[PDB]
Amino acid sequence: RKCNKLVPLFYKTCPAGKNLCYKMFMVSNLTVPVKRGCIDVCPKNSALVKYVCCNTDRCN
Image 1 (cartoon, rainbow, N blue to C red):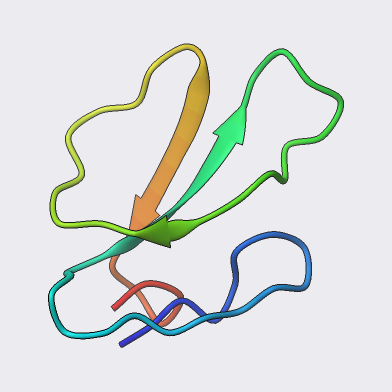
Image 2 (image 1 turned 90 degrees about the vertical axis):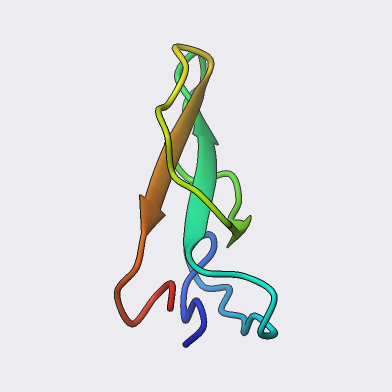
């Protein structure tokens, strides 16, 4: 599939060279929403950016 979410109101598709989608967010900030893209592997997440990878409807 694709990522019917990125940010609050953004939605996208992926092509067929990627597996999941993750929203890249941040921890120092005032929000929680920031972005998303696709992914090939979800390892871990840093203490700088919120990798909320997922493989559901909003991912693949």
